[PDB]
Amino acid sequence: XXXXXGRXXXXXPXXXXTXXVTXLXXXXXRXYLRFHXXXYXXXXXXX
Amino acid sequence: AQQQLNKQRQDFERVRLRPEQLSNIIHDESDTISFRSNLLKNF
């Protein structure tokens, strides 16, 4: 019906500023250290 | 055997750093100062 010259345009529904736009194509119209290895009792203990 | 050195250090320091108490700790003045008696005397 609406198809024009081999083009299948059929599958279409047919029934501030106020600009006007064209329809169908819109455009303007833990762990804490332990004592060892912490450097005491490694220089100490006079007993 | 680094744990044995640590146990020895603990035994030594528990004796060295132990605080005296209710004994020869005897205090000077400015410690045994009664504020109440001075206030009464001045009154």
Image (tube, coloured by chain):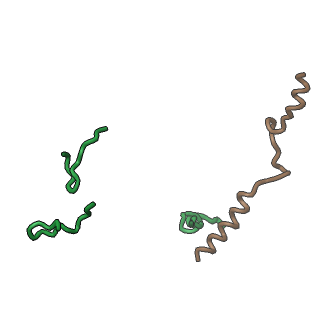
Chain colours: A green, B brown
Relative image position of residue B2 (x, y in whole percent): 58, 74
Relative image position of residue B21 (x, y in whole percent): 82, 53
The quadrant of the image that shows the C terminus of chain A is bottom right
Q: Report the number of discs.
A: 0
Q: Residue at x 79, y 53 (%)?
A: B20
The part of the image, by quadrant, that contains residue A5 is bottom left
In the rendered image, the residue lying farthest to the top is B43
In the rendered image, the residue lying farthest to the left is A5
The part of the image, by quadrant, that contains residue B28 is top right
Residue B11 vs B21, above or below: the answer is below
Q: Is A9 placed left or right of A40 in the picture?
A: left
Relative image position of residue A2 (x, y in whole percent): 17, 65
Q: Which residue is drawn at 56% across and 66% down?
A: A30
Residue A18 vs B17, above or below: the answer is above
Q: Residue at x 28, y 41 (%)?
A: A18
The quadrant of the image that shows the N terminus of chain A is bottom left
Residue B33 vs A34, above or below: the answer is above
Relative image position of residue A22 (x, y in whole percent): 21, 50
Q: Is A4 placed left or right of B43 in the picture?
A: left
**Closest to the observer, A44 or B42:** B42
Q: Residue at x 59, y 67 (%)?
A: A34
**Closest to the observer, B12 or A2:** A2
